[PDB]
Amino acid sequence: GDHIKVIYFNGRGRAESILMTLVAAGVNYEDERISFQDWPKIKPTIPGGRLPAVKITDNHGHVKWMVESLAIARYMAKKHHMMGGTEEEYYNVEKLIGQAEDLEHEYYKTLMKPEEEKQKIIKEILNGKVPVLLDIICESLKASTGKLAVGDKVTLADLVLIAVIDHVTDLDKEFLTGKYPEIHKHRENLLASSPRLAKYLSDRAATPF
Amino acid sequence: DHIKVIYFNGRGRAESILMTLVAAGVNYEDERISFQDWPKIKPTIPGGRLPAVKITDNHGHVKWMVESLAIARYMAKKHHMMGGTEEEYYNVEKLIGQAEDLEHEYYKTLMKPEEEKQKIIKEILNGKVPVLLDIICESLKASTGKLAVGDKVTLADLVLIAVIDHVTDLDKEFLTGKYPEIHKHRENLLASSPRLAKYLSDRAATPF
Image (cartoon, rainbow over the protein chains, first blue to last red):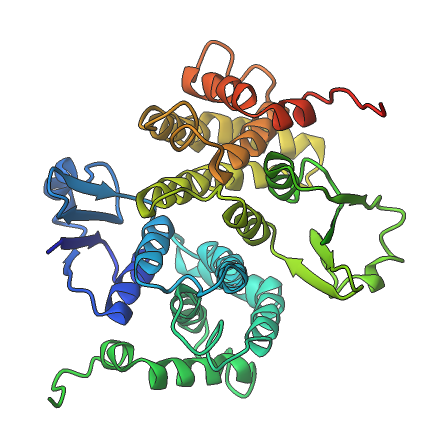
């Protein structure tokens, strides 16, 4: 069928929810993680200006090149029924993606910085908007009609939430300890609801038939 | 349903919602809240941030929406403005994201004393802004039609008006003689959409 290549610098970077969407949907793809060293030779080909980029061979005629990570992710989720089952649900999928991405924006402030400034910024955001944005996410989670971000089925909102919360806990490994129960539970419910994600996100390896 | 859109600034974050409703021909009530009226008011809105949309059905039941671009996307999806196929949907989302990458630079100028605002304006306008506009132009060039995505109005067209207008707010002649695709898109969009041309150029009314 189609051959999907996901091309990215960091697997837990911008492309993460593209990766997770395909995994959740049971769609085959090839990882193409590009090192700092291999980039100058890879760049001329991909797309070729900047990453993440996705190369899809299928149609036929021709190959498709895609950029803008969350555009790609929404496309993939939509194609695989993960953008909501109704327009109502679609709204709530988008609300949580937006709310997750509001939190992601805080996290982004910490990137490409030296340790001293980095730690300063981290302390700034963790005692700034991060808690507020985490509560809004907890509220959104609380108002779900089901066990997951929106309903009982996997949506892109679930996947973005994994990505973004993991970035927050990279900044501070204990920021969520004893707090934000909805977010802890959401992660547990997600992995319980999706064997493919549970396998992938725990690096599980030896799957029984 | 009665739709009331509640916001501080008509050309702020609620704008894409307002434009989506207009382009769709959906009647709605404006509730612009001045800074003086906000603490009043604030308590009235769950909880307790703008933009917000209050939906009242015919039986008086109230539903709330927050997160502007999620609301815009909902409105647009309901009124077939999110693309007509899976690939159009992608190009719509691609353009929204690209427009929002540009919006992000613009956000740096907000709530700053004129002194550092003009410094920030000058850095973004000589930094990522041209790059981001070049990207939007290319996506516009790649359209299969006259608008952002194909020939019909999508949320991509609307967010593009919002964003570009914020940029020219910073610098009124930033696009002059440049970015022809952006100039043309705006022309094509208002020509394609009488409702949007009327709203956006502040025309008429009638009554009657």
